[PDB]
Image 1 (cartoon, helix red, strand yellow):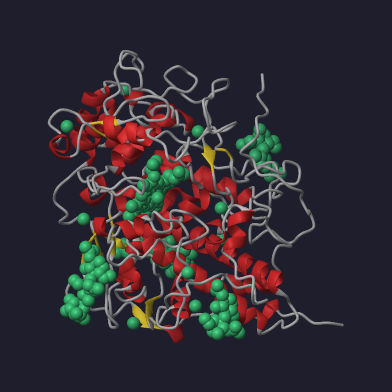
Image 2 (tube, helix red, strand yellow):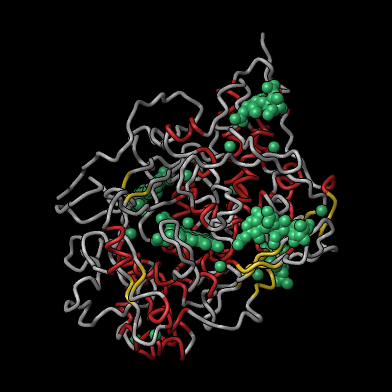
Amino acid sequence: SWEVGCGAPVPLVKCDENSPYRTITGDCNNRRSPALGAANRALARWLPAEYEDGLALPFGWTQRKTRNGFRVPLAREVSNKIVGYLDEEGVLDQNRSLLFMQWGQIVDHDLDFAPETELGSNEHSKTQCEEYCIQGDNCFPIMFPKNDPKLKTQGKCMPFFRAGFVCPTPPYQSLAREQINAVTSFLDASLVYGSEPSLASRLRNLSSPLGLMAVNQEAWDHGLAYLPFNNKKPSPCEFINTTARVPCFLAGDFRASEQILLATAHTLLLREHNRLARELKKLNPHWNGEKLYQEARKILGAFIQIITFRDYLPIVLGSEMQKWIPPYQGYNNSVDPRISNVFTFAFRFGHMEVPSTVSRLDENYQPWGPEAELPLHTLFFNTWRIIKDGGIDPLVRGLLAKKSKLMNQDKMVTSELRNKLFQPTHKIHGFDLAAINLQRCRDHGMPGYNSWRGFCGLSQPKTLKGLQTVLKNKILAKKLMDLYKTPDNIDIWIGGNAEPMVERGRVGPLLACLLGRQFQQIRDGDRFWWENPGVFTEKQRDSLQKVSFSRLICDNTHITKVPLHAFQANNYPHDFVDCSTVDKLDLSPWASREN
Ligand code: HEM
Ligand SMILES: *[C@@H]1O[C@H](CO)[C@@H](O[C@@H]2O[C@H](CO)[C@@H](O[C@H]3O[C@H](CO)[C@@H](O)[C@H](O)[C@@H]3O)[C@H](O)[C@H]2NC(C)=O)[C@H](O)[C@H]1NC(C)=O
Ligand SMILES: *[C@@H]1O[C@H](CO)[C@@H](O[C@@H]2O[C@H](CO)[C@@H](O[C@H]3O[C@H](CO)[C@@H](O)[C@H](O)[C@@H]3O)[C@H](O)[C@H]2NC(C)=O)[C@H](O)[C@H]1NC(C)=O
Ligand SMILES: *[C@@H]1O[C@H](CO)[C@@H](O[C@@H]2O[C@H](CO)[C@@H](O)[C@H](O)[C@H]2NC(C)=O)[C@H](O)[C@H]1NC(C)=O
Ligand SMILES: *[C@@H]1O[C@H](CO)[C@@H](O[C@@H]2O[C@H](CO)[C@@H](O)[C@H](O)[C@H]2NC(C)=O)[C@H](O)[C@H]1NC(C)=O
Ligand SMILES: [Ca+2]
Ligand SMILES: [Cl-]
Ligand SMILES: [Cl-]
Ligand SMILES: [Cl-]
Ligand SMILES: [Cl-]
Ligand SMILES: [Cl-]
Ligand SMILES: [Cl-]
Ligand SMILES: [Cl-]
Ligand SMILES: [Cl-]
Ligand SMILES: [Cl-]
Ligand SMILES: [Cl-]
Ligand SMILES: [Cl-]
């Protein structure tokens, strides 16, 4: 019946059980089941996997074997016929700041990460793949359909490598393939501190006994810190401008430099740690480094949970928030905290919220310079624009003043991402994130669209007319049917995002259900949830419900004007107020006394 074990990629050491602090690997959160929610374990399955050979081969791998009677349409073709659009006019969200999109990518990276398989570097299969598009082993190419412009310009495919799985990393067979989640499942700010002890330690400043995080020594942002540079050459960040040779940043998560605005947010969090750390030393001079580090790390973890659950989720889920996430009632040690495989695709809805340009604003929110509005694709793994071109402040003003892209059925994913995505392994700005998502969907063996509608207790359309009704769109339904032949075959990623948004939210009914369950589970199944009695004191808690992203900005940048509600669309200068008007985090409740 049960396959209750395999376990090598699985970090391992004892629990303190009385320690008031989370471990780095997530281990020991649950006392009865210690590895529950830990990093480097398999992603949870809410539904049985669906592979072509029922074991590990993804659908579309063998070109003669169908899925429910039909061939699965090429990922790229679905991308071309349904996901793309040309006109960026009128695509912006009239009531969601650019920060709304950016916070999601943060939360996301704190929750899941399914890295690609290795099988060595000095490899020539990493070459056999992008070079000859030969499917086999972990190379699973995204072929181009006929009439694709990339055929004339890029080759016959886009290389793609399968995601890592448990038990090993190499040639495996037995049980059904299960992907790895290299990060901790709890909302614990592991994207700032790391998910491995090795990496957690390297990020720390273990010279001064101040419990500070290591900062860049080669550059400063007007007296403020930058994350240290990465050790690793060759570096993607310097590849995109060999004259500036500015390496990628080093952080608790390896995706930190994936795009300038994500690197900006990471910098804000690293700065807040140090601020909290030296601010604490000022109240408790006897406390040592470890103590300063852990007590800071704890506040920051609580901070991320509060903004997320109090300001972020209510405006994603909308009126469905209360339906899936009822008021907190206490830690439930029986709740499965782990991130499911499907969540890592459902949370990718944020990809349709990314706009095609990033702006830099000057002190009183005017265009910063002449090349102030930049195309998104010039910013992937671009760190030199931060170091050499103004610091983070100008980028932060743009997060508050500019808007997120609104999901639109006739305009899903901007071309900056759909045709010009830059991958760290490769050299070109010619990848397609939408095609990647779909090929990945299949790589993870995801059940079709209708299996998930059933799971969420929602109708399952079997016909065209039925699909029109659910999507409330005749044209979109048609295209989907033409490519998939049956709703049963629609990949969850596009199926889920193709649904119209629920009242006051930004995701449809299927997504709201998937997102909702997961968040309820990681709150309820987290022994260290900030509201769990005994984790913080009542006074420490009254002091924490006063935090805000605005304040975080005021305390860690030289910006002096900020909106009160950073997540909603704000117009300068009316909606903006002076920093000294916003509530500070009162740390006195963290002071101690001797005898
Ligand atoms: C400029 C903005 C962004 C870029 C360039 C970007 C890029 C990427 C790339 C390259 C992947 C890996 C795909 C794969 O190989 O399977 C990925 C994964 C993902 N992204 Fe994004 N992303 C962006 C924004 C966002 C946002 C705003 C959200 C949510 C609000 C989000 C959620 C996710 C999730 C859930 C994954 C899968 C992670 C895993 O392995 O567990 N992303 N992104
Ligand atoms: C732009 O987006 C905003 C959110 O979608 C929207 O306002 C939000 O509506 C909620 C409705 O519940 C309100 O939130 C709080 O309202 C009162 C305060 O007066 C509280 O006592 C309640 O507990 C509730 O949480 C706010 O009015 C607002 N939400 C937040 C967090 O501020 C705006 O109206 C939207 N603008 C337009 C033009 O649609
Ligand atoms: C690669 O990075 C280069 C620097 O990291 C960058 O060049 C820099 O940006 C512009 C050049 O276009 C110059 O900015 C302005 O500087 C002053 C004005 O304040 C004047 O000298 C000029 O008017 C100039 O426009 C920087 O001086 C320049 N720095 C260097 C060393 O060239 C490149 O644009 C980047 N190249 C690519 C392909 O990304
Ligand atoms: C570790 O922390 C120490 C203490 O702040 C840092 O040293 C200070 O850094 C700058 C010099 O670059 C100046 O403020 C002083 O010279 C130093 N002060 C003291 C008291 O030594 C050090 O830079 C940090 N190291 C890392 C890698 O982040
Ligand atoms: C703790 O959460 C678990 C789910 O992880 C809940 O378990 C339910 O237990 C009831 C009986 O009390 C059964 O009817 C169901 O089989 C369980 N439901 C689910 C969704 O698994 C339980 O309700 C919670 N326990 C407490 C005390 O709140
Ligand atoms: Ca985490
Ligand atoms: Cl799943
Ligand atoms: Cl096509
Ligand atoms: Cl700083
Ligand atoms: Cl450095
Ligand atoms: Cl990424
Ligand atoms: Cl909360
Ligand atoms: Cl370019
Ligand atoms: Cl029907
Ligand atoms: Cl709204
Ligand atoms: Cl300002
Ligand atoms: Cl807000």
